Picture 1 (cartoon, rainbow, N blue to C red):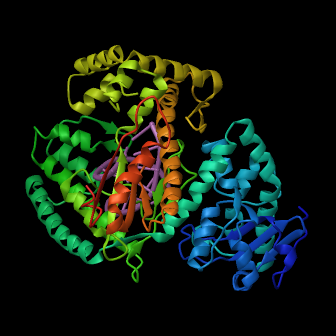
Picture 2: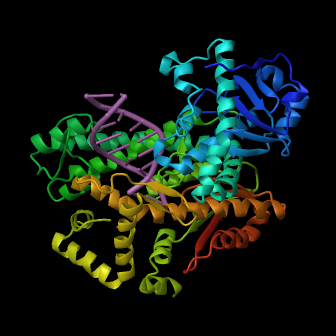
Picture 3: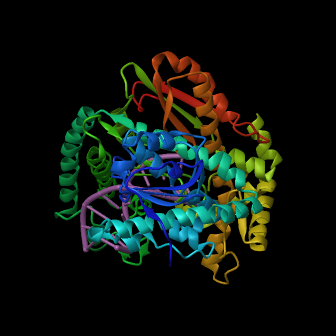
Length: 546
DNA sequence: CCTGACTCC
DNA sequence: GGAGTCAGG
């Protein structure tokens, strides 16, 4: 463990080379408006650590950061890019992201620091972040020399690992997936996250006031029906009320006790009316805790904006996730919760929200992959590896009739049946399944002798190519869309992606254009054997974009 | 801290 | 099938 570097006091010309590994260290998990604690640069000329107060106020270093012809290899470049946006600095020229490279090679490793990526190539001259910063309340930036060494070691690791990772991606036919899709998408997501979405806090607070009143009412009604006060938000206490006091049938247990899941409670409605009230209560309580209170807590008060983080290197299928706040699970199915969307508004006066969604993209993808004539034919003119049991439990119908449904289904769509058979056999033979744009998921459990383990892996084999291909497509569509927006000099920009949906805001005068541009681009992102279809709506709030 | 509840795709 | 957050414990 011997590695020389310069702890620099000022920026020098040799630090500004046209190819470098760059570390812009942000220690907080949520990098919005978070401190940059240190910088490291490794390039042909040497290894350098820079204090951010120095480097970020240096016009030549800022210039270098923003120069796209000066190429940087990084790890989680979006964290750096956004943290620098909050410092009013533009980051360009990112040509390699070790995080996204590691993610494509194997999503299951859950790589989230340089040390874990390095482990994939047996590179061990770098420590884990957790080792250096510590955890929980003990989390702290160490003394400068210890910090400096770590940052330089991380940059040095990125320097040496770039070619080995690129080499393996290319052997996997995933190099273009990294360079032409994930990496450009990363810059787009950074834009969306920094832009944020404006919230109508006056409206959200008034909703919370009315909701608190309504919860109280429902709560007292439940106690009345139960004959006793108890904590409705405790499945344990609730279980005692339902299955001991009221002596309702026990339909399901889990490892900790009686199940009070929504499915179960719905099936108990013919026994006691309290179960319908309880389901209602738990819905309203989630609205209050999460979409009123939890959302207000993360609103930046001066701008009334919320800034999510789209985790690009987390899910096993290639989807994004959204955290702090999650803006990909805002209520829509019940009118009571859907009204939450009235609180999401345009960031400027006389702008509107525009929302466009793919219709049944996973079913069109299945049609394409399976080349099922009947299914493809229908699309030119169901989501349930569900079993007869799950289907019956889902539809609250006869398990015998459920079995007949699934049977009839594969009779009618023999291409889909063939596909399900073939993809499982392929997974067993190769050890992984792949998506349309060459995303991979490894399934080492697929030949387990244990029924449950094997079966879960077989269902992943069936679903991942479908769900992950749909992810591939919308990602490409975002890249295509952004470009067309910039070409036409539109002010419209993306705010959110919700898996098979894109949400934008824009001057009212641009709706007409977007109504043609967004759907076309999204539909023409890839050519399948069936058409892609997109629906679109716009309005004064997200609610009204329906 | 995990579990089980609600939320979305 | 894929996700995140919350209260309770």
